[PDB]
Structures are given as structure tokens and as C-alpha cells.
Image 1 (tube, rainbow over the protein chains, first blue to last red):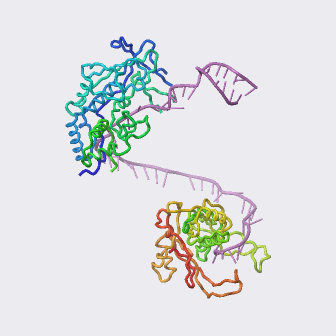
Image 2: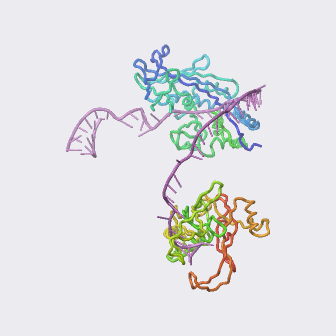
Image 3: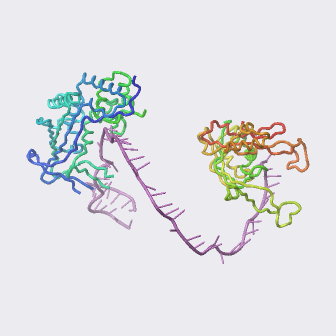
Length: 292
Length: 255
RNA sequence: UUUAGAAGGAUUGCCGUCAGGAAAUUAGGUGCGCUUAGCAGUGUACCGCCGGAGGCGG
């Protein structure tokens, strides 16, 4: 008996990312030594003459999906959403999407531009008081998604269960070690002071906005119409709109709006790829409403 | 083509007649159709075959020559009389008769039907609208002469339509009482002149403008009318005036 | 082929003197703003060389 989406429907994000803060260190004494890394006034940022490593620290909080609806002005549609998410938790325990997220952590895509010309990159992931074995970060590629590593599975199981109910929260902390070399530029983020390139400062030091680190970890969509022609992962957006190649990659029937209209407002079993895209859009969040 | 519609857009007229023996204001409709028939006759001597069988009158601004008193009434002006033929013609001061003059900005909608209705016809109209007058007044400037297709190309303004039902259907013993009461009830209507009636029989007198045609002594007839905006108009045929001739009656009607 | 066709309104000027707006007041009780997000066309255009303006090397 459902004819349309409600006049107010919104979700919240189930993957919360903190802002990054930049540090400098040496490499053979990296586990005993840290120094501030500051902006030099156009603005610029460069390492010192005695350090050869940039350390980037940030953390992630994972929340359940079912208890992440902020507004729904029709109880029936809420009952429909809760039953559909329970159906997906029966088939797949949110393992594919979470495996892809931990893979995007391990490939070190969160070091945009800061990654070209590095010599050794390592990334350690800590959950609770137990450190996990580090990642080589250059034995991975930005086109493929590994599914047979041990630690990636062992983290993605924890993230999964919590996207699905069995745990209420998960706090994940990640540290990185990029060896670009002495007296080389840093490339932190940039502010729309809205002249000159005003760089971002976080607690005196430099860092990236949390939105850029989030948009690096949501490039997991390899289930779009024209993927055989252009073979590259895109960010998980609504009317899929990767800004580099300035052409909408999903303008039409496979859009989130149509696809969720053809799953709640008229029962129809989508393929598993389309479910894997919709349950993601829900992990991101937005004002998915209507103009009734 | 054959049928078609041509717009004469934003025409400025200076010093047109505004006196029709009981009415001081908008000129009579016969002059506005006389402009169209004169345009047809000059276009048919240049060998551009065309026939205009309907005019629409849109009003954008007006001004009456004179001033408005403190009490809110209008006092009209006249030019100084010069020399008038007759007995007292070698005198220095002449006599003052009854007259009134108005300035108008208007747009005309013409329904033309000929062997070809193209933009060359619009150029031919543009080369002929600089020798004619409108209601005894000179034309100062115009914006454009263009062809229209629908009721969305017509510019913003207010058209004049015939409302004879609001006269024939009012309370009074005679027609003048009907007109006064119909003007007291609705205050957006104006009285207009709509043609002539006959007082004699057709024949040949002595002293005519053209001595080889048929003559009849006449009296002007009057009616009611009102204004309607462009965006609230239904059809493009409910704003077009036409000539109609019975026996003894010379009229202009929208029908 | 238009209630057609025509038209010099013009010269001059002292508005002035005086004045009490004034007394009184009760604006009040309630209340969810709130889901989402990557700032730059390469971040600049450097030394010379011919050659009386137009060119060429790194």
C-alpha cells in the first residue's frame, strides 16, 4: 500500500572519520620520536633538513545501520526498510562492503598526491589494545580488491558484525609512515578562505579534512552500467558523478532514487549488485526525501 | 501562404482627434480601421496583393493635451487658430471652435490573407507606414514589424473589446439612461463610437469630395466597451474588429 | 482612402505681523532546527642568445 517516499527521510553516517594531523619523524627511530610539522608563510609546507618521514594519524568510529535513521514521517516505510535490511543481514553479513573498505584503508588511498614518489609506506591498524600486523601499501593496486589476506578478513569481520547488530560500536585507529625524503614538500589540504593558497591548520600542525579521508574510503563502486569500457572504481555517490571524468556515470534507471523506489514502493528482487549499492548509499547518509 | 497575422509594435502617435460630439477621449474605431484600409490601398498600388480583414487595438500608454485641476477634473487645450477660409479671412484673429487632442502608444494586430505572407511583406509595410497618419496624427517612431503565430508572442498590454450585452441588459426607459446606469454599476467600462447611421437616401448632391460616387448624410452611433489584458485573453479572434454593412447602417463590430 | 485637409497664447509683479499641547498608566504566560559533503587551469611564467619589430636554445 505504499505510494511514495515520505516528506522527511534522512539517515546518518555509520562510518565516522576524524581529522588528520601531520607529524614528522626519522625512519630508523620512528617508534621513539616525533616532532611538529608546521606551515611556512601564498602559503607552503615542507619538511625539515633532518627528517625523512611524514606520519599521518586518524581514527574511525563504526555504528550499526538499523539504528541510524534520523527521521521518517511514515511508520509503514520504516517497517519496510527494517525488513529489507534484515533480509540482507540474512544473506551477506555486510562482509563484501566492509572488505572493500578495509582494502581501501590498506591500499593507502587516503594519502592523495602525497603518495607519488614515496619509497616505503607502512600502515598499522589498531583496534582496542591489540596492534595488527602492518601493510606494505605498495604491494596493492588501486584497481583490484584483494580478498584472501588474513588481517583484512579479521578486521572486516569485526566491522561487519557491527554494521549488523552484534556489537554497538567499534573504534579503529590508523597510523601511516611515508618516506618521501628530506626537504620535500608535504601537500596538506586547502581552505576556501573565499587571495592565495591558504593551507589548513589543525591544532597548530597541518592535516587533511575528514571529508577527503572519507571520500577516499568510499571508492568501492565497481557495479555501474559502463564498467567494461571504463574500468576504474568510482566513489559511491547518488547520481554517480566522479568529478575527474566530468560525465555522470549513472544518470538513469540504475540511480539510487529509482532503485530504492523499485525495492520498497513495489516489491521486486534486485540483483545482488544493486543491493550492494543501496545498502552502501545508506551507510553514507543523506536527505533522501521527496517534494510531495 | 494565405492567412496570417502581422504585428505593428509600439507605435507613437501625436495629436490625434479626440472629439465625437458627446465623447472626449479615445478616437473612434472607424479611424483605426481606416488606417488599415489605407495601408491596403497603398500596398495594392505597389503590386503587393494583400487584404486586411481584421484589426486588434492594444493600448500601452496615453496622454491628453491639457491639465488636471485640483478638484480632479480635466481641462483641455487647443492650438491658436490661424486663417480659415470664408468671409472673415483677411482678419488677424480667427474664431475658436470645439476640439480635443490626445497622444497614444499602441500596437496593432492585422489579419492578412494573400498569395504570399512573408517577411518581404513586412518590409513593404515598413516602407509604407512612414507616409500615412493615424486619426489625423503623425507617426513619430515604431519598434518592429513582425509576424506572430500564437498568443504568446503578443507583448503586454490591454486590448479593447465590445460589450453590448451590458448595455442592452440594464435598467431604464431609454438607451441613454441604460448607458448611465451601466456606467454606474461597472466602473471599468468606457463609451465608444462604433460607426454611422443614415438620415437620408442614397443619391447625388452638389459639393462632394469625389463627384462620381454615392452619397448619404449620416449621424454617428455610440456603444460601450472595456479592457482586457493580453494574458487573460482566450482566442485571437475575440479581439479583432471588422466592417459590417446593413441597409442604412455602417458598423464596426467584434463578431 | 481615417468627424478628411489648416493653426505662435503673451508681456509685468514684495503675502505678511503674533503665539505654553498637557495631565495618567503592569505586554504577558508556552516551545527539539536538522540529515549530508574532497578547492585551485599544472601555481606559476626562470637564466641567456640573435639582432634593427619579428625570432630562437636550456
